Structure formats: structure tokens, C-alpha cells
């Protein structure tokens, strides 16, 4: 009702300036007395700022997908961030270091949506019919806040720490795909930096997409045909460094490489 | 061969048999890695003397992260024997154990003998079938703080093993999901990719380690490739299950209090 | 472009058109281009309009400089595009008249058939995957209107990215269940391997180049349309073709295609 | 008398990790001469306690052959000390100046001898796998000599193999990505090995019968290099990704 306040616009502007100057800032949770709702409002102002610059909302990212991580942040539910055409990377493409900000990588299942989920009370059945295929993905999260010092208010206001998203090229339909026991390994320089399984992502990647679909319908911004949903971490995040090449493999889904350029 | 080697082996073997913890070596009982090797052999000889036989091998520290955390430069292996076998779907009394933990693993059945410096290629040519498994591990020492030589002498905590269904040897086990659960709720989540980045790598290492002691992986051996997740303390009255992508599940229970 | 139909551009386009009709390559036109790569595309565009005026049909686009090595030898860090017409189309095994080529060179490529129009701004990989119907094994026969292939970025783009003929295979293969990053490529002539490659050589992946092309076409006001065929890029080195030559290209999991040149 | 000292200086270079000059004028060798240095070169490794475990074909291309002015392939015997654990690490200090190459490896399940067809060859194969050859010329600043390369055992030094794949796997045209720390250094296809790897196995058996040998059961055959060799350097992850055959890797130690 008051999402477009002077306080929110100041916080949104701060995070936006941090991204442009490539210089992180002090935490903002101390300036948010409105709870996670005010943080979502702050995220929203930067979403409109990106739309007003002619960018395209290409999807959403789901965060806090394990009860362990929800518990550290004092929450009993996941968080969501907004993806844009500028944040997209294809498997193997060089990632310019200036596109990251304290980058970390997480292997996830990307779900492409082919039907709008605009109605209230979305079910798992609505989500299955609206899901076209899946893609192996590596999310490259980033932080506009200094040294990743973030509570739920900081991350949600900072677009749930979204940076980039790396997607694979070969789609795989849900029929004949077991996303619960799908094994995950992410490697860097032949080393296993992240280990996981589909079940780690809220029990199943569709449990997270179903959570998001309904959260978005209550925020007045539902999922749309063509949107890519990054369903959540399959394993722990690994901090990325210039020139790093992480390769994630999801059993039955495929592989994807995030290549960071140096300097 | 030494009086200390015999004294520690016998002490470690009764801890196992009684299910009561025994203290670690400090100063007088301080042991060489080479001393632990001899204690490891006598510890197994005690079991063979009671009628058990060697039936396989288990690899320990099967990840560079693991060797890094314990400051080691190679994995540890343990010898498995007919008496550590647990019927899949069976029950175990925690009373015959000191403080047992459960780990999900990938198991290989050798169809032919495997010896020496082998390629992944040559390793799987001697494999008959593959299966998911759970290793029940038990450090026999009391108030244990990590010392490499103690675990070698304590047979790398070998104590129990349970295996699942037969699967073709060409099954891809490089990155299968794993869910270990107590009473249906997950206690550990991971992938068989945790075992050296590719489980066949552990089978190659087992031939390497066994050749060091002039041994070989004989036809019919059960090789536990390594732990895909961290071990979990077992409790009484629980159903322990291991579910693996494309491999089915395996289970066993613990007696009630 | 505000002046893509300049008197200068028309002269250069007619020069290249004439070089092709008389089967006689001309000298490099890079000296005459001062507006850079944009002026070169205006020149290719004039010749496109010339072909449409003769009742020809645009059937797709070709992508060149799909490797960083080749990009570097032309002083650029991006690929180029050319326009394909129905008259350039060849089927697997069909005899190719020598008159239809000009300094012909062969390259194995992955052909992508489009089934949806990508007319909007900010086309994503998701849009492209949804607009790709299937793929065919292809052999591009490039040609130069500039003599002895003495070309720079301006000569090739202006000369329709050195486009010639495109030989397509007959059997479609859907993308789901097709690994184009690791697909092996071999092109043989008289039992010899004349070109070797993999899908990754084409800008990392054929869909990487096709996403570049779709995006560039929207910025030039000529978007990819349904039915268009995209010659995504070389999977290996170019081999000069001679009369009577038969080139076979195999793309593991995609199929094979033969380019047979007539004996002139 | 001469052959024994060339063999020993060549052998010296390998255990030492230090380069040695090419065979010139006085020590100049004949293909035949180079043949005995190679046999004696392997004899030194045997003496040290290693055994012959396979073969490696070189110049496995008509282009590579014509480029070196030869009409046939060359090979080198593989010994157990050249084995490198897959996923392992190597110290470059033990090498004079080594390069890596991606190949196809066949594990022979039965003996193969003589002039064989492609059909008979694969009937003797237990499995196939992707592989990487670690090559190392022992010569310092080498100006190509056929006899030196033969006498230097086709620069054989290291070899690593990937996972078991069924022997009927079509390895005729598989994509190969050899990379250093996740970035490709070489891009190719298995089609590079003579236009079909099974042809290198055929040639491997024709060449072994040339000297009264045979491809024994359980041997390892490295069909050939599908791409150009890339020089190795410290602290790098070396991986070979092959279409339908998975990948294999090994590291180099840092300074």
C-alpha cells in the first residue's frame, strides 16, 4: 500500500548505485522496519528501475530452499528474486568479471514455464501442466552488500542476491525424469566443490516452483509463459574467483559450465 | 612383530567383541603408521581364528576434501570379513557395538581378480555387478580424537556392512543421488559422485592399496567404494534406509530399547 | 541505418552483383568503404533487395567468424551474417553445377530450422529453443566475389558474408536428445579427412551463434522468420572445392550430407 | 655396440628428466638401428621391474604421415611405469618437457595377431574408453628425425584411461574436448585417428606381427592422437571430454 515510499526508494537507490559502481555497501536490514514485505517492496522498485531501462523479466530465482538455511535466517519459507535478460549466460560463454559482485555458484534445476499461472490457489497439477521442460543450471548469485553480511531483509531487498544464471542448451521433459533422486556434482579444476541431490531443493524442485508460483500470484506478478524458474540450491554455494570454471552435472538432466573471465 | 603390537591388537579385538570402548595410544602405546598396519593384520587374524573369512575391502577418506580435513595424503582401507555381514532387511542390536554410525556407499562385486595399477577401464572389466550399500562403522576407541595410525590399527572402523540389489556392471554410478533415512526422514543427502568424483576411482585405488601389501582383489570380493555422505550415529528402534538413483534402496533396522 | 541506400553503397552492391553474374571476382572493395561494418551490411542488404526484386525468396541466414581464432584474424570480436535464398539451396547428393560456385570452399555445419518468428527485442536462449523445430547436417559452400579470397571484414560482410550454396540433409533430428556441444564432425573427400571438428567449435554451441544472429537481425529490422534455415557456423576448417569433387560430412547423432560438384 | 649407448643415453634422459641431443653423424641411426634402440629402451624399463602393457600408434593420419615424409605409422611399446592413475597428479620435474594428447583406448579381451579386418579386430575387444597420452621427446630442441623418434620409442612416457564402455560403442566420429583448467586447448573428433579408430587397432596388429609379436589378451591399445599435443605446465587440471565416452582427468603439481 506504501511500497513506493521515500525510505524504500532511498534503499533501492543505494543497492542500485552499489551494483553500477561495482562497490558493495553496508547492510540495509537496519533501515527496514516493515519486515520482509518492505524488503520485497525495495526489490520491486529496482525491478521497475530495470524495466524502465528497457530490460526484460526472464524469470525468478528461489532462495532459502533448505530448512537449514531458512533456520539461519529466522524464516520458515523460501525467498524469491527477479531474473532479467541481462543476467542470462549460456553454457560455456565467458562471464565478464564486471558482471559479478562477490560471486558464488550453486547448481540448480531450471524449469521453463509455458503457461501463465495467474490464478489464485495454484496446485501442483497446474504447475505440471504449465511446465515445459527442465535445464541444468548454475546460478551465479551476487551481493551488493559488503562481505555477504546479510539477513532476510538484506537479501530480499538485494533481489534475493541474484547475479547471473547459466543455462544448458538441451531441454528434458518432466515425463521420465526423477528430480527427487537426481544426483548433483559441481567441480572446479577437477575438484568436487559441491555435492547434492534433487531432494535437497525443498524436497523436490517442483515444491519450490509451486511455492513461488503462488507467492508471485499474491504479489500481483505471476509466472508467465517463457519464464525460467531457478528452483533452488541442490548443494552448497562455492565462492567464485576470476578465471574460475565450474561444471555442474545433474543426473538425467545434463551438464553446464560457468566460465569466469579474469581481471 | 612386537609385544606392543600383540597387546593393542588383542585390546582392539575385545573392544569389538565386547562392544565396550577402549582407550587410544598415547606415548607408550603411541604407534607408527607401519605399526598400525601390523595391528590391522592381527585384528583381522583374530576374526579368521574364530571362523570368519576375508570377503572384501572398504575405502576410507574417499575425497580430497576428506584427506584435507584429516591432513592425510592417501585413503585408508579396511578389511571386511564374513562376520561383519548384515542381512539386508535384517535387525542389529546396538548392544554388540561401541558407538556405531551408518554411511551410504556403492558396492562392486568382483567377477575376476583385479591386481595392481589398473585403469578405470580394466577395473570394470573384472566387475560382475554393482549395488548400493550402507557401511556400519565403529571406532573402538573411547573419547577418540583423530590420529591416523589409530584408525589403521582399528581396521578403519570396519564393523558392519549391508548391500542392496544386483545391477548391471555398466550402470553409470558416477553421479547418482543418495538419500539415507532413519524412519523415513532423511538424515543425509548426497550423490555417489562424492566417492572420489567417480566411484570407479575407489575401485582403482583399492587395487593400488592392496598391491602395496602384495595382496589383490580376488574374484568374488565385495568392495565398498566409499562413503557418499557423512556418517550418522545409529539409535535403537529405527528403520535405516538407503535409496539411490537408478539402484533401488537397501535397508536394515536396530533393536528396540 | 539512415542512409543505407546511398549512391556509394549502390555502386559497390552493383559491383559485387556484376562480379557474380559475370563469374569474375573483382578487387577488394574495403578501400571504398569508410562507414565500417554497418556500411558493409547496407551493401549486403542492397543486394538482398536486388534478389527479392528478381522474385527470389530469403530462405535463411549463414553465420561466419564463429571461432575466436578467425574473429581475431579479421580484427573483430563478433560473428558476421549472410542471407540465404532459395536459389542457393542444394539437397544431399544433388549434382552441383560448377557455374553455381565462385572460388568454392566447403565447411560442415549444423543447420537449424526455425518454426516461430523471433521479432522481439532481447531474444533469449529460451525463445530460440522454443523456435527451433529441428536440425539438419549441412555443408555450406561459401564463395567470394572478391578475387583470391583477399577479404577483410568489410569485403565479406558486403559480399553477403561470402555466402554461396547450402547443402542440407534430408532427415530431420529434434534438439531434445541431441548434444551439439560434443557432436563430432568429419568431412571426407576421396576417402581422405579434409576437415575435422566438434559442435563446440561453433562459438561453444550452434545455438550460441544462432542466438547471436537472431539478436543481430532484430537490431537490423530483419528478424528470423518461421521456416528459415540457420547455417550456424563452421564445425571445422574450410576446404577449397574443385570440379568433380564429392565431400561427405558426418555429424555424430545428426547425420551425413554429401556435396557433389559437377566437373565443369 | 653403438645401439647400446644410444639406448642408455635415451633411457638416461627419461629417468633423469633432462633432454639429450638428437642422433648425429657418429651416433646417426638407421630405422633398423632405431628399431633395436627401442627394444633395448624398453629392456631397461623391464630390468627396473616394469612390464610391457600395450601399444601406442603415432602419425595416425595421412596428413600427419605426409607431413613427416613417411609411408606408414610408427609405434611405441607401453610399460607399467608409464601408467598414471585417472584423477591423479604428476610432477613435471620427472619429465624433460612433456605434452598431452587425447586418444581412444581399446582393452583387448583376446589375442589379435597379423593382418586383420575391422570386424575381426573388435571381436577381440573387451571394452573401449577415452584416454590421454602424455608424450615426452627426450631430445632437446628436436629437428624431426624418423629414426630418432622410433629409437626414442615414439616419445612414449605417460598414459591415462577413462571409463569402461561397451565394445560395440561407435567411436568413429566422437567429439573430443581436451582442456586445461576447464578451458579447451584442443577441439576435435575421434575421426581424426585414421578416419576410424578401429583402423589403428588393425594397423597396431599388422605392425606387431611385423616384429613377430601380437596384441596379447589384456593389452591396452592407444589408437592415436585425435588432436595436436598441448604442452603441460604446473598446477593445471587436465581433462579430456569425449562424446558418449564420458571424461578422464589428471593434474600437474604446482610449484
Image (cartoon, coloured by chain):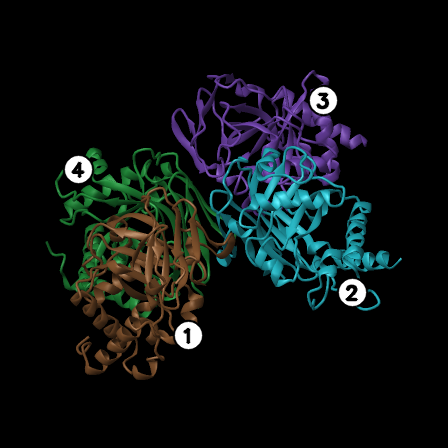
Chain colours: A green, B purple, C brown, D cyan
Report whether mark 4 lies on the same chain as mark 1.
Answer: no
| Residue corresponding to mark 4 | A122
Q: Looking at the image, which is closer to me, C188 or D95? A: C188
Q: CA distance from mark 2 to mark 3?
A: 62 Å
Judged by depth in the image, the label closer to the viewer, 4 or 1, is: 1
| Residue corresponding to mark 3 | B46
Q: Looking at the image, which is closer to me, C17 or A163? A: C17
Judged by depth in the image, the label closer to the viewer, 3 or 4, is: 4
Report whether mark 4 lies on the same chain as mark 2.
Answer: no
Report whether mark 1 lies on the same chain as mark 3.
Answer: no
Judged by depth in the image, the label closer to the viewer, 2 or 3, is: 2
Determine the residue positioned at 82% across, 46% down: D47
The disc at residue C148 is: 1
Q: Chain of mark 1?
A: C
Q: CA distance from mark 2 to mark 1?
A: 44 Å
Instruction: Tell me the crowding category of disc 3: few under 14, some 14 to 19, or many 20 or more residues within 10 angstroms, Cα based.
Output: some
Q: Is residue D89 left or right of residue A31?
A: right
Residue D152, percent across and down? Answer: 74, 57
The disc at residue D23 is: 2
Determine the residue positioned at 47% across, 42% down: D244
Q: CA distance from mark 4 to mark 1?
A: 65 Å
Indicate whether B38 appears above or below C219: above
Amino acid at each position: 500500500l506504501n511500497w513506493m515510499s521515500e525510505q524504500n526508494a532511498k534503499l533501492a537507490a543505494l543497492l542500485n548505485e552499489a551494483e553500477l559502481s561495482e562497490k558493495p555497501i553496508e547492510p540495509v536490514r537496519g533501515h527496514i522496519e516493515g519486515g520482509i514485505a518492505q524488503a520485497y517492496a525495495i526489490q520491486q522498485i529496482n525491478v521497475q528501475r530495470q524495466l524502465a531501462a528497457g530490460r526484460r523479466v526472464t524469470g525468478r530465482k528461489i532462495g532459502l530452499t533448505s530448512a537449514a538455511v531458512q533456520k539461519q535466517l529466522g524464516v520458515d519459507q523460501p525467498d524469491f528474486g527477479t531474473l532479467f535478460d541481462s543476467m542470462a549466460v549460456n553454457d560455456g560463454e565467458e562471464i565478464a568479471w564486471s558482471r559479478t559482485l562477490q560471486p558464488k555458484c550453486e547448481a540448480e534445476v531450471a524449469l521453463v514455464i509455458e503457461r501463465d499461472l495467474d490464478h489464485e490457489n495454484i496446485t501442483l497439477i497446474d504447475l505440471i501442466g504449465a511446465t515445459a521442460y527442465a535445464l541444468p543450471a548454475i546460478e551465479v548469485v551476487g551481493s551488493r552488500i559488503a562481505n555477504w553480511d546479510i539477513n532476510i531483509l538484506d537479501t530480499v531487498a538485494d533481489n534475493a542476491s541474484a547475479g547471473l544464471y547459466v543455462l544448458g542448451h538441451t531441454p528434458v521433459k518432466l515425463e521420465g525424469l526423477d528430480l527427487r533422486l537426481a544426483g548433483m556434482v559441481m567441480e572446479r579444476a577437477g575438484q568436487q566443490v559441491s555435492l547434492g541431490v534433487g531432494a535437497a531443493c525443498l524436497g523436490h524442485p517442483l515444491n519450490a516452483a509451486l511455492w513461488l508460483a503462488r507467492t508471485l500470484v499474491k504479489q500481483g506478478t505471476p509466472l508467465k509463459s517463457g519464464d525460467v524458474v531457478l528452483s533452488g540450491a541442490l548443494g552448497p554455494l562455492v565462492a567464485a574467483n576470476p578465471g574460475d570454471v565450474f561444471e555442474a552435472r545433474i543426473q538425467g538432466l545434463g551438464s553446464v559450465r560457468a566460465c569466469f573471465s579474469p581481471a | 612383530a612386537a609385544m606392543k603390537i600383540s597387546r593393542i591388537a588383542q585390546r582392539l579385538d575385545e573392544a569389538a567383541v565386547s562392544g565396550k570402548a577402549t582407550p587410544q595410544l598415547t606415548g607408550d602405546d603411541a604407534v607408527t603408521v607401519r605399526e598400525a598396519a601390523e595391528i590391522q593384520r592381527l585384528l583381522i587374524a583374530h576374526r579368521i581364528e574364530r571362523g570368519a573369512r576375508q570377503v572384501g575391502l572398504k575405502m576410507g577418506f574417499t575425497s580430497r576434501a576428506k584427506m584435507a580435513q584429516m591432513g592425510v595424503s592417501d585413503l585408508i582401507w579396511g578389511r571386511l570379513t564374513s562376520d561383519m555381514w548384515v542381512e539386508e532387511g535384517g535387525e542389529i542390536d546396538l548392544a554388540h557395538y561401541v558407538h556405531p554410525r551408518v554411511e551410504p556407499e556403492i558396492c562392486y562385486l568382483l567377477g575376476k581378480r583385479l591386481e595392481g595399477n589398473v585403469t578405470p577401464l580394466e577395473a570394470l572389466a573384472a566387475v560382475e555387478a554393482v549395488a548400493p550399500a550402507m557401511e556400519i562403522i565403529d571406532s573402538r576407541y573411547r573419547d577418540f580424537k583423530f590420529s591416523l595410525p589409530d584408525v589403521i590399527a582399528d581396521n578403519a572402523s570396519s564393523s558392519g556392512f549391508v548391500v542392496g540389489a544386483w545391477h548391471k556392471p555398466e550402470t553409470d554410478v558416477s553421479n547418482l543421488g543418495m538419500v539415507m533415512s532413519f524412519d523415513g526422514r532423511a538424515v543425509e543427502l548426497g550423490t555417489s559422485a562424492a566417492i572420489l568424483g567417480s566411484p570407479i576411482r575407489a575401485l582403482v585405488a583399492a587395487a593400488r592399496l592392496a598391491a602395496q601389501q602384495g595382496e589383490a582383489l580376488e574374484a568374488g570380493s565385495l568392495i565398498l567404494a566409499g562413503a557418499a555422505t557423512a556418517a550418522v550415529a545409529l539409535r535403537p528402534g529405527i528403520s535405516v534406509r538407503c535409496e539411490v538413483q537408478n539402484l533401488g534402496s537397501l535397508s536394515f533396522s536396530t533393536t528396540g530399547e
